[PDB]
Image 1 (cartoon, rainbow over the protein chains, first blue to last red):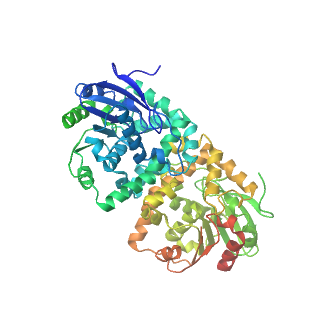
Image 2 (cartoon, rainbow over the protein chains, first blue to last red):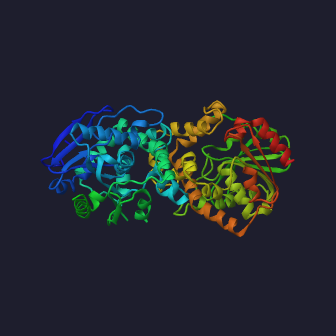
Image 3 (cartoon, rainbow over the protein chains, first blue to last red):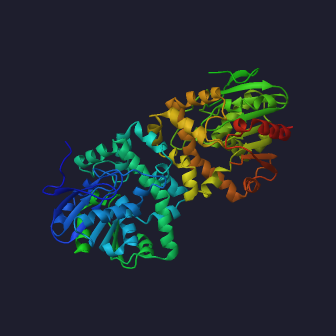
Length: 289
Length: 289
């Protein structure tokens, strides 16, 4: 049976116009929403959430279509899995709890939801943290031979359905575990709690969840990119106080996108809250308090 | 599996790297035809007869493709580099007593062919390349748009066993979708069903798929480096050359790479000899005559 990795946290299934959002909820104090990325679920925050819960009301949510959140039906523009749409849905969910102004930290896809939210609806956020990302526009602008080989999955998972879905079907466990291992410092699964890996594996084993992940990357290649392109070619900057953390220039990039940003490296591969939970929790606690 | 070359013999040709399979027909000046991915020598079955009216036509499976032997690869993918493939096919042609011949290639085979022309121009009387630009150029062009359009250049080049593992779940689906996707029609209707079965049978073998991935790995690394040396040195192919391409700039590009080249678009997707056999055969006959 899948483990409870958030001792003493409650659970909520929050209704929205686009479907329910699952979350674990703990602590007390100013509200802080935590958003995971790919190929993970809310449980990736399990090593830093208890520390944060000592000072904040912590809401640990599954992204639209991920984990135990509902999977809204997609369309030809991948609309519900665009970061603009995901941000709107999570804004609705937070209003159900009575939170109209809150702190936000995101990792990977969740971080993309977070900066898009800040660009579209800055009034919703007191402060923003993004973990191991640059804006989607910047990833695509950097596209050349070396990058194309290094993060091939941005273009692979974005191929029209059912191409990646059919490739992922034969042996999903192998793909999701190889990706998890690939982006860590050690290149294996040693950084992860095995109980957390099982959450990720069970999610990836559902073809409907895998289809959502592909719709997310299709949005990442198309509408998300176009939304970002508008902002950069207008010189729009996030006005929300912001923190950028990254694993082993990023601050120079984010300074183009944000007018009040600070940043620091964290000695980690990609999965900062699992690979470097102590440094990551300290950074987030310091910034948000 | 059907015989699609009436009158042509079937030969296994020995080389220091393993046997090359070919269908051989006609009489007159020697002409070698080289297929690409994900196909075999049979892709020439519509145009080979018209060519055999005027030439001795040798329709070869690339090293590691079709019925040709599969030499053991290595960490630099050496035997599936276009330089090595060209050396192996020069050995095969010497077994037939052909040390100066005409050459037409398509896709991967066209990449073997222009590399052969750069390394060993004395081997060729005339050169035709079908629906390609040099490997260097395609990588120089690899921005967001190209990363999405030719994603398989980066996907198939990922370190083993990532693409081998994915391709094993439903190879028939993948190969048939590639064939369809790259035609003007967007379905399999331009192909002879017997030809498609040859392609499917080949692609069903894990060892053959592994060769294909080694070919794309060479394409991302050593083939690119070999081409880069020539571009920087200003080396041009001196062999009289024809560039044909599917209409669904190329002559402008090839003129940077060759000092004597003609070219034309064909009303066709990628698979010229099957989608537009009459126009392709006429262009080739007129050129090589």
